[PDB]
Length: 275
Ligand SMILES: Cc1ccc(Nc2nc(N)nc(CN(C)Cc3ccc(Br)s3)n2)cc1
Image (tube, rainbow, N blue to C red; front, side, top):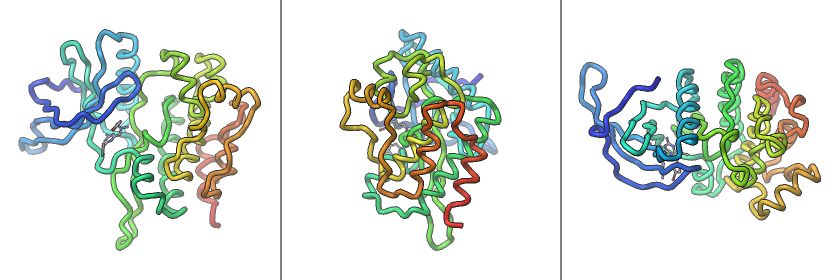
């Protein structure tokens, strides 16, 4: 059960765009913080129409269950505003935003070791979720949030978090799942009830492809029908431009869900690259 935030303490400043049946804003939350200090905290606001009751309930149940598992690589949600005809998730505002946009804005002038570090951090988050048997179901590079850039002087690496899960693919329209190929795995295209921890291993592979491809979207040239044929003919993605993780990508994007490796195994594989 999330902390309730009053509409009166939320200021909406910028309209940023949309997610899946959500509207996204930058704003400020007025709050009493540590030592009783009054703060105006920057927040990322995700707004759902309460008339889409099934979507809203799925969205907030997913955010709540994940926010019960505090972890350094899982986004902080401050709470929720049951805000009239809308329900609003109040999330921390991450300074550098989504990783796919970041990589594009930096023109993929990012070395493989940076990419490896981000993959290790995501894998650490996913291992924690796996140990907690919590399915995320929407792993993608847009949901990797960059808290801090690398600092070459100190040797500090970039630092990421994984965003909230959003509406479950067990509730979303089939057309949305197909648009989300190749993040949504083939078994969930066949039947969304096949959602399983194995789903996240597949999507982790697709996410690593995105990271290695500078924020390109795999299969962007394919409409939904060509994306179905992609899975029918059992194709794999092409090796990304930075090919060091291509084997891992393909091992995670296994058409047999039960064969996808555990996140402990994935981490050991990541740790073994470059001796
Ligand atoms: C330009 C800029 C810079 C930083 C941030 N900060 C941020 N903080 C959080 N917590 N999450 C996100 C990304 N998630 C996927 C929500 C969004 C979906 C669509 C958009 Br557009 S933002 N961005 C946002 C915009």
